[PDB]
Length: 312
Length: 312
Ligand SMILES: C=C(/N=C/c1c(COP(=O)(O)O)cnc(C)c1O)C(=O)O
Ligand SMILES: C=C(/N=C/c1c(COP(=O)(O)O)cnc(C)c1O)C(=O)O
Image: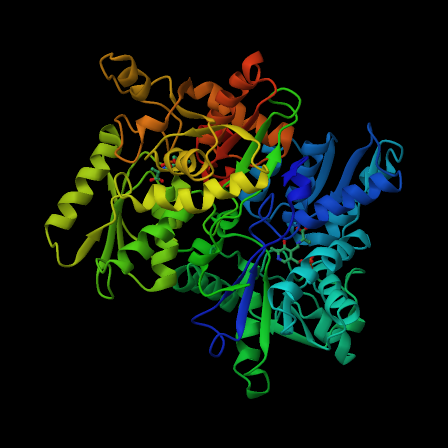
C-alpha cells in the first residue's frame, strides 16, 4: 500500500541468519536499521506521537519535548516534520556527531546537555524546559511513556512471531528505556502464549539491572555502548518479564559490530554488537544449542562513523 | 521468513505519499534507503553476485572488481562479506567521505581515482586492474551487466505494481547506470502491460541523455548530484523505453532533499532531491495532475553528512 506519511511505514524489518556467530544458525538478527529514520526507535517516535494525538495532549501549536541518546530524538524529529509539529530535544553532548547533525537537518531545537550527567542530565533538562512553559510543551517521556513498549507489543513482537513461524525460543535485546524487550516479551509470552527466554543486555561497566536483581548496590558507570546502559532502572523496563540479564563490555561490543560488518555484511551499530555478543554466548551453551535465538539490532553503522566503531 | 544471508533480504521497500510536493498526493516516493546496505544498489549488488555465481564466472578464490560512485560498491561489499569473497572497487576520490569509510569498514580493497576523470576514470582503472591478472579478478561491470536491470525488472518494478494496485502512471528515476529506470520500465510496460510514462532524470549541468535524443553534441559537465549524471550514455540505459527526460540543477536537487527531510520527515540523499524536483514539475502540469507518479529515492541522508547536503 501507500503510506499517508513516513510515520505509518514503521516496522516489518527482516530476520537474517548469522553464519559466523551462534551454533549452526540458531542466532538470527532483526535489522531495525531498516526503518523510516533507520532505527528501532522509529516505531516509538511514531506511536508516542499518535497516542498523544489520540488522548489530546498533543495538538497543533503544542511543541514536542523529550530526552534522548539520539535515535528516539531522530525518530520523533522525522515524525514531527511529517505531521507538522515543532520539537525540542535534549541529548548528552557526548553522543555521536551524526545524531547531532541529523537532528539539526530535521529542524530540531537541539539542547545538548553535560556529558558527565548522561541521560539523567538530559531527562532533567527536558523537565525544566517543559516546566518553564507547560502550556507550550508536551514531554513524551520515552523512559516511562507506555506508548513506547505498546508499539513493540503491537508490531515488533508479532513480526518476530510471524517470521519465525512461532519457533522463536529466546529474545535478546539491549536495554535503554526497556521498551523493546518489554513490549516484545509481552507479545510473545502473553499474546501468543509461548514461554520464551527474555534476555536483557547491559554494559558490564554499568550493570545496574544485574546488581538490582542480585540485591547488590547499584553502581552505574561510563561505557561506549551508545543507546543502552542509562545507569538506572527505567520505568519502561518490565523487570518481571526478564528471565536473564547478560553483561557485555564496550571493547567486545565494538569488535562484534565490526565483525558483523566485515564477516556477515550487516551494517550494525554499536549496541547491535553488544546484543549479538550476548546472544553468541547463550547460543554456544548446550542448553540453547537447538533453540532459536532472535536478536534485536537497534541501529545502523553510518550513525557511528565519528565513534570508536570506525577506529582504524 | 528468515533470510540465509543479508543479500536475500533486498527490496520490499515502502511507498510514501508526499504532502508538500505534487498535487493532492499524486507524488509517491519509493524509499530505497530501506535496504540491506541502505540504497537501491543493494539489489544489484546481490543479483550481480548471484548471477556470476550461476554462470560460473564467480567462484571461491575469485576476487570481485567494479567501478562505483559509492552505493554499488557498498552494495557489492556487504554481499562479498556475507558470501565470502574478496573485493576491489574503484571510485572517484571526490565521492562522499561516508562512502569511503564504510567501504573500508566492510573490508574492501578501495582504489580512489582522479576526481577530474569521474566515472570514466573509475571504470578505466577497474579494467586495467582486471587486465593485470584476469584469472584472479572478475569485473561485474554494473554499467553494462544485464543482471543490473534484470533484478529491477524482477523486484523493484513488481513491488511498484503491487503497492499501487496497478495504478502507477509515471515512474521518475535519476540515471547513473540506467538499470533502475530500465528494469522498472520493462516490468511495468512489458510484463504487466501498462503504458506508463518513464522519466529519466539527469543534471542540467551534464544533460547527455537530453542532448543525445535531441541530436545535439554531447557535452558532459561537473555537478553535485552524487550517483547520477555519469557524463555518457550507459549501456544499461534502455533509451527505447524512456518517454521523457527531465533535467534538474544541483542547487535545486540539494534544496529539495533538505525539504524532504525538514518538511516530509524523509531522510533522502541528494539524487533523491533531484528525482522529486523533476517529479514535482510533472505533477503540477494539468496533464499529470490526476496521474499517479512514483519516484525512486535511491539513498539516505547520513551517507551525505560530509557533502553540501548538510551545508549550514
Ligand atoms: C533511549 C534511546 N536509545 C534506545 C536504544 C536501544 C534500546 O532500546 P530500548 O530503549 O527499547 O530499550 C538500543 N540501541 C540503541 C542504539 C538505542 O538507541 C534513545 O534513542 O533515546
Ligand atoms: C552508479 C551508481 N550510482 C547509482 C545511483 C543512482 C542511479 O541508479 P541507476 O544506476 O540505476 O541508474 C541514483 N542515485 C544514487 C544515489 C545512486 O548511487 C553507483 O553506486 O556506483
